[PDB]
Image 1 (tube, helix red, strand yellow):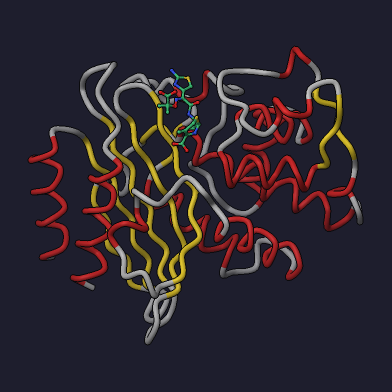
Image 2 (cartoon, protein in one colour):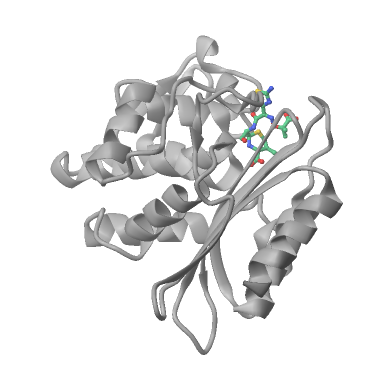
Amino acid sequence: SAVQQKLAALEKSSTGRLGVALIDTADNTQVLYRGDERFPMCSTSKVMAAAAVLKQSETQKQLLNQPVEIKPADLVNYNPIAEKHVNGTMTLAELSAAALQYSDNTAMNKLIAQLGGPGGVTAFARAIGDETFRLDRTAPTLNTAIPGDPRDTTTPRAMAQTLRQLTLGHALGETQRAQLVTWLKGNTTGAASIRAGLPTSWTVGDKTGSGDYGTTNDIAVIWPQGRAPLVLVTYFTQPQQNAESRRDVLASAARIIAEGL
Ligand SMILES: *C(=O)[C@@H](NC(=O)/C(=N\OC(C)(C)C(=O)O)c1csc(N)n1)[C@@H]1N=C(C(=O)O)C(=C)CS1
């Protein structure tokens, strides 16, 4: 397709490896670029952990209101919210919001721990039919993004399908699904990524990620005007370990999609 050709041109010009999956829910068509290759998720994996905790809350009724102690040993590399509550508590709802909306890595580790470790996050993915996602490490090391390493990876196609099931489909109960969508719409870290390639009148929920190798990721549910919602995954990684982040490349991928489909 013409969109695939433009994504290939974008990838070649940008000097990296680009993975894109678009689902258009108006007609369930899919546009993929390297859609079945594995990419490091980086912090985009926080969506799966938050969703798995919401799933737990369907049977543990007010689990989201439970206080969780934040201890010094919990702090990692980037903890903009949790660092204000060390030797205190945050609820699981507060940890989920911090993880999703600020990409707080300590908050993510509390979610992972609440699920029984990275294997528990992966088990949730399997339970909703995602056979591709794998979470193998906690924060911060899940973001190393070393080429050739299959840990903490998924494919664009699998992640787009899962994000659709979580936000638009039936993987979560109605209250939980609404809560996930509210959290994603409130993300603070995505203004330069997929959102920057879309008209400002469209509504977006997204979760970013970044890591070594200039890895720059974003996954989004988009509610345009005038048409049904879209699900878009954009993953990008580069050959040099200390390559600079390219959020603008993701914005350009989103613009190609939003103009071409
Ligand atoms: C999610 O992807 C998280 N990423 C990281 O913790 C790591 N790096 O983030 C960047 C911004 C690239 C950094 O230079 O520190 C990381 C862990 S281990 C390793 N070798 N790199 C958080 N989420 C993002 C995001 O893109 O949403 C951030 C900007 C903060 S960290």
